[PDB]
Image (spheres, coloured by chain):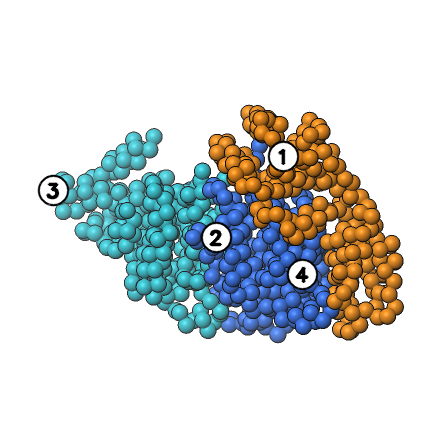
Amino acid sequence: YDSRVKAMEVDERPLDKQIQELVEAIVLPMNHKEKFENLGIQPPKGVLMYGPPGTGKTLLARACAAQTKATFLKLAGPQLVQMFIGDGAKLVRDAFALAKEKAPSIIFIDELDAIGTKRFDSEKAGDREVQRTMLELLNQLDGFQPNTQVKVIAATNRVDILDPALLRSGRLDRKIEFPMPNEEARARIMQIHSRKMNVSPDVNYEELARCTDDFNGAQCKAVCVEAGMIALRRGATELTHEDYMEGILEVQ
Amino acid sequence: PTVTMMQVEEKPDVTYSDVGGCKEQIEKLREVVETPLLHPERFVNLGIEPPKGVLLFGPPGTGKTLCARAVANRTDACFIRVIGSELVQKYVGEGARMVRELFEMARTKKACLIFFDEIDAIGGARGDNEVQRTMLELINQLDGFDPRGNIKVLMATNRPDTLDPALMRPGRLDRKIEFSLPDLEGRTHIFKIHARSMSVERDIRFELLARLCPNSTGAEIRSVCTEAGMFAIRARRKIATEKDFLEAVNKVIKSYAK
Amino acid sequence: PKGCLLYGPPGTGKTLLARAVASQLDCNFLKVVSSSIVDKYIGESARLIREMFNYARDHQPCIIFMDEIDAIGGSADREIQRTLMELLNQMDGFDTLHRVKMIMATNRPDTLDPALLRPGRLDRKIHIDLPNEQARLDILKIHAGPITKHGEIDYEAIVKLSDGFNGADLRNVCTEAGMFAIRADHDFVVQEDFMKAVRKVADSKKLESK
């Protein structure tokens, strides 16, 4: 029933200061239950990956899901907004029923601050049953001790709206701030994202690294694929060095 | 609906060199609509994948004709086009099985090219959830590489006020170029290859008749090329001369374009 | 005795105790959302309000919880005030509330409808600023069981050097120091990382306690 939310996406598989604690904080709670039972440590459930734009949290967390290799489920923010009623029990108990019974998967969501607004201005707003959905989320992630099952990963593009009652292991606990890392790191993750193609063995990474400023990872992959667009018709079967900065100065 | 029987495109039509003045853009789109099919191995060995596609919007001009031209100049098997004016109809919900059956036929056609026309009839998100299901399910079934993510991406629309396709198009669509309206010296090739009809006298200079018809769409100049032989045979003659229907030309554009 | 208010300005604690009793017995299992009142559409859900309260009065045992009420207690307003009048007619009407019990919870005690704060509706008021340290020491003793520690132990530094916190905060900081101790792959965990890590991280929670 309600295949629009039940069968959302049938998928199996798709900066060190945050990807270390992130990848560890999502991989070690999966298998390393022995030390969790020896030292009594509880696996973290909620994580707040916030910060300014220009980083690409969606594709970075998607790459983390590629590092986990487990099942991945896609879900967006405004997808909970539906004209029908009673979506809290049906959607929360449905997605948490398939996640409750099925194998341990990974559920990464985004745009949570917009749908998690407590309605400061009470003039007129329909965002009241999505607030019901949030109260049932904190209800089933707070009042249920057997909730050591499949985690729920959240991501917010801004911290303008923040519920002060989100202080719990099951709730948003790992407040990951974006310190705007160095450009060479984006040239490293982009170097890994572009090492498969035939690249000429002369790249200094200084120009193409410095040119990438406040640019998400999806835009960097748009620079790589965009470089492959004209690079396919350049005649040479190997990518050149000026095509990175040409793509940045072409679509960016 | 009529989109199932009207969806299949056949009966070839207006050919390549009748483009509306586009000299660079005809290569910018030919390199993705004709070159990948003619050289599949050259794009796999010479690079990583063939190009995705182009994007034509803005002024109407000769729109909706160049894609039928791409259907005409197909060397292997004419592809299927999809219009958007049939998606927004009463009793919504059939668009899911519709896009799944036309994409299912696309998988039945060894992943053939699928053109999408008139995105503005289902675009412009700005009670509209029934439209959001069709357009968000469509974009979900286009950006999603599960059926195919390499065939073709092209949206020929008139109004660019579509908010969601404008932000979702950087995912898989590309080449945010304009329409490149036909210039003055563009129609001379339309006359050159449209001279393949009944024997036309060589006194008709194609540059003069081409430059004496401004602001004329591709369908308009096609109707002029049809009325040239029409008003040329209505006189029970055997040859066509510009002096026989010049008044019909400058009248059919002037009196009908004031 | 037909109502009670639990307002804690610092941190939490109403959901910890409401979850301790509501998770212990609760006399039933039926949670009522304190935000799904009117509608998302035209306000014709009076059959849903009188249906939910119709079941709350149909069943003999019933306990209703309402959390985060400060957002709903602030043409579009005439229906809000009309539903507040419906709450006045359903809480102080011709219906003896001798068996049903309701508990209201909030976040900031500044906009709690002083008209609704009249005695009779919310009779009991308790400040959870400093919970006598019994919840802190108790949650620290139940969280100190499975974790192995060295013989050198001093709970007075953790209980005394931490104020204005709760059980969930203290368990997230104690487990945060337990992860800080598991990063160094050591078997035993001394309380030095508890005093320094819980002290400094606790100061970061005091700074980020907005």
Q: Nearer the viewer, mark 3 or mark 2?
A: 2
Q: Secondary structure at mark 4?
A: loop
Chain letter, disc 1 residue:
C
Q: Residue at x 39, y 42 (%)?
A: B121
Kind of residue at badge 3: Arg
Rendering colour (chain C): orange
**Distance from the alpha carbon under mark 4 to that under mark 2:** 25 Å
**Residue receiving disc 1:** C98
Q: Which mark is residue A44?
A: 4
Sequence-earlier tag: 4 or 2: 2
Q: Is residue B8 above or below residue C10?
A: below
Q: Residues within 10 Å of mark 2 (few under 14, many from 20)?
A: some
**Residue receiving disc 2:** A5
Q: Residue at x 41, y 48 (%)?
A: B134
Spot occupied by residue B116 in the image (x, y as percentages of width and height): 38, 51
**Distance from the alpha carbon under mark 3 to that under mark 2:** 70 Å
Q: Residues within 10 Å of mark 3 (few under 14, many from 20)?
A: few
**Distance from the alpha carbon under mark 2 to that under mark 1:** 43 Å
Q: Is residue A128 left or right of residue A181?
A: left
Q: Nearer the viewer, mark 3 or mark 4?
A: 4
Kind of residue at badge 1: His
Rendering colour (chain B): cyan
**Residue receiving disc 3:** B236
Chain letter, disc 4 residue:
A
Chain letter, disc 2 residue:
A
Both marks 3 and 2 on one chain: no
**Distance from the alpha carbon under mark 4 to that under mark 1:** 43 Å
